Image (cartoon, coloured by chain):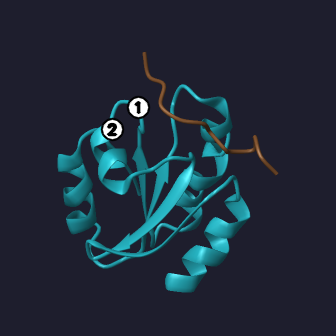
Chain colours: A brown, B cyan
Amino acid sequence: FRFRYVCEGPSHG
Amino acid sequence: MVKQIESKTAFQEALDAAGDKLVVVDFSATWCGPAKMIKPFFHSLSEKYSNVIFLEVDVDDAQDVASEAEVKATPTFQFFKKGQKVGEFSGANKEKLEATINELV
């Protein structure tokens, strides 16, 4: 698997 | 040109081979959409700025690079030059990569 922390890409704004 | 960093070994070598041009790194996850969502920009600048070096890092398969950079939010844009850091900023802002690059160019 390959998961780490949150992806605040176009997810936040 | 673009360069993929799969191990801390290619990281330092990427900066050494970057010469003296600017060096922006994209700490994006290949499995996460929101991060990879900004690839049509960061990686696109590769053809609009052939005078700048663009790197790529997998915060999950290359925790060695993210570990040393202590990244905790993707995508994280880190700027290096001659192996030295000069600036950095995360948060989906592809338009800023332009202003930041033209800043420390």
- In the rendered image, residue B84, in percent from the top left (x then y), is placed at 30, 75
Image position of B49 (left or right of B9): right
Q: Closer to the camera, B24 or B87?
A: B87
**Label annotation for residue B46:** none
The crowd level at tag 2 (other Cα within 10 Å; few <14, some 14-19, many 20+) is some
Q: Are marks 2 and 1 on the same chain?
A: yes
Identify whether A4 is placed above or below B66: above
Tell me the residue at 30%/53% (across/down). Answer: B68
**Label annotation for residue B63:** 2
Identify whether B95 is placed above or below B67: below
Image position of B24 (left or right of B15): right
Label 1 SS: loop
- In the rendered image, residue B105, in percent from the top left (x then y), is placed at 49, 83
Identify whether B57 is placed above or below B2: above
Q: Chain of mark 1?
A: B
- In the rendered image, residue B46, in percent from the top left (x then y), is placed at 52, 58
Kind of residue indicated by mark 1: Asp
> What is the CA distance from the residue labelled 2 to the residue labelled 1?
6 Å
Quarter location, residue B40: top right
Label 2 SS: helix
Q: Closer to the camera, B98 or B29?
A: B29
Q: Which residue in the rendered view is the most extreme toward the top?
A: A1
Tell me the residue at 62%/66% (across/down). Answer: B97
Q: Quadrant of the N terminus of chain B?
A: bottom left
Quarter location, residue B31: top right
**Label annotation for residue B60:** 1
